[PDB]
Image (cartoon, rainbow, N blue to C red):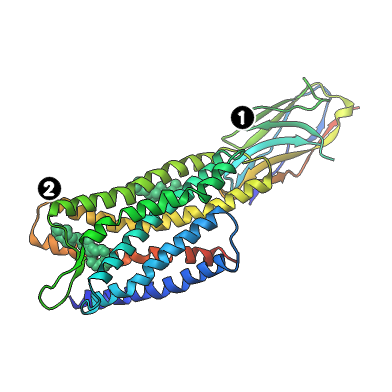
Amino acid sequence: QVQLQESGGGLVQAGESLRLSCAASGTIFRLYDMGWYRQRELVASITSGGSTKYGDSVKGRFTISRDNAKNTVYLQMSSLKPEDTAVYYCNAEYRTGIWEELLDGWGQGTQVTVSS
Amino acid sequence: ANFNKIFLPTIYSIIFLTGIVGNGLVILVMGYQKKLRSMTDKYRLHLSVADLLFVITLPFWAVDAVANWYFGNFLCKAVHVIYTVNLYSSVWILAFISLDRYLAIVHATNSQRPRKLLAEKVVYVGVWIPALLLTIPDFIFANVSEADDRYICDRFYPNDLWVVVFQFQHIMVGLILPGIVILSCYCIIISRLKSVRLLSGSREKDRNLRRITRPTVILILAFFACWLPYYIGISIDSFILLEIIKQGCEFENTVHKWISITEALAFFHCCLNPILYAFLGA
Ligand SMILES: c1cc(CN2CCCNCCNCCCNCC2)ccc1CN1CCCNCCNCCCNCC1
Ligand SMILES: CC(C)CCC[C@@H](C)[C@H]1CC[C@H]2[C@@H]3CC=C4C[C@@H](O)CC[C@]4(C)[C@H]3CC[C@]12C
């Protein structure tokens, strides 16, 4: 199959900048959609074509990115708020072959904390 | 020529038994036991009928290759007609399968009508009628000679120009026209598969489309891989006819051996549908 991990968490002061990472490697035939969640709260998701679908609570707040070469997705955080302290799960949609169906995936998780 | 005299009947009999068993099983199962699923199964039923006809006519060719021909001019004409009908029917039912898949995948919204009509009222006109009409030269030319010793059951054209014309049209139609149609259809299909995130509008429809599509790809690839070397051999032979290719007399006998052996090995196309059913029927 494929492997996905998450990183970028830790104890960070409010109003700082960081970039979460989620790299997929292995039996990858194609990656279709990659996004971060928080049930399943859709906070960000960038299609392979770049047509991002940001969340209502983060409209104009979060910035997403993707490197097709490294199969990585980056989340640019800025202007931290206490209500945003949560654990984020990397979500991606992949395929293992031309004749294989659409397979969903999930990440381990990253915890982001705001100082208070 | 003892090697060829022993090699030909064994292959013509192995293919005969396998064809009878597999094609009879497929025809019975999909004609009376009602295991037909979709249009691809109808096309495979037509393929099985044509292959059953050719497999039935094979033992006469086996006996002809063994010793002689004690069957008659009428049977010579019948076997030639059956061979031509089977060849032209199968090579174009494959193209009809390809067109069905292209319409199913590329235009997936309103393909039901030009996916049902094209198989319910158009396959006969598109496949069988031209196949039947192409056998008029078989009626005219197929005969039994009375040469020394053996009796030969082949086609005796009055002049070599018609020989090269018939070889060229056989190659042209039955390798290039379905070849080009299949190339276009499957190039578009593969370009769609690698790009579209989700065919149709649901995951189940997508996976159904992929699962139905793949066996036809395998079947077409195997069919063309079987038939290609014979076409290469007869292309070289035809270029020997037209004063282009000229080498030592060893080349002529080498080409004769190559073409005979490769036709024997290329008659294996009749055993493809049962083998794919066995592979993908668990
Ligand atoms: C075809 C073409 C040829 C090439 N040539 C023919 C004449 C032109 N070539 C002259 C000039 N070429 C110089 C060298 C020619 N060497 C081969 C002769 C050799 C073999 C075949 C195939 N079968 C082989 C017979 C046994 N098949 C059993 C089933 N058959 C069912 C019907 C097909 N019956 C055709 C004959
Ligand atoms: C035009 C004449 C001379 C030859 C016709 C041969 C055609 C029908 C055959 C020969 C080689 C075949 C291709 C070989 C490899 C591939 C790649 C695979 O991922 C999808 C099928 C595909 C694309 C095949 C489609 C059918 C094919 C193109």
Against B274, residue A31 (above or below) is above
In the depicted view, which residue is nearer to us: B140 or B14?
B140
Q: Residues within 10 Å of mark 2 (few under 14, many from 20)?
A: few
The furthest residue to the right: A116
Q: Is residue A80 visible?
A: yes
Residue B149 horizontal side relative to residue B132, left or right: left
Q: Position of residue B52 (x, y in %)?
A: 42, 67
Against A55, residue B243 (above or below) is below
Q: Residue at x 50, y 61 (%)?
A: B45
1 and 2 marks in contact (CB < 8 Å): no
Q: Say which amino acid is labelled 2.
A: Ile
Residue B252: name its quadrant: bottom left
Q: Residue at x 54, y 46 (%)?
A: B117
Q: Residues within 10 Å of mark 1 (few under 14, many from 20)?
A: few
Q: Position of residue B244 (x, y in %)?
A: 12, 47
Q: How many marks?
A: 2
Q: Secondary structure at mark 2?
A: loop
Which residue lies under the disc numbered 1? A49
- Same chain shared by disc 1 and disc 2: no
Respond yes or no on whether mark 2 lies under 8 Å from ligand 1: no
Q: Residue at x 42, y 48 (%)?
A: B126
Q: Position of residue B224 (x, y in %)?
A: 38, 55
Residue B222 horizontal side relative to residue A24, left or right: left
- Quarter of the picture containing the C terminus of chain B is bottom right
- Quarter of the picture containing the N terminus of chain B is bottom left
Q: Chain of mark 1?
A: A
Which residue lies under the disc numbered 2? B244
Q: Is residue A101 visible?
A: no
Mark 1 against mark 2, which lies toward the viewer?
2
Q: Chain of mark 2?
A: B
Residue B188 horizontal side relative to residue B229, left or right: right
Q: Say which amino acid is labelled 1.
A: Gly
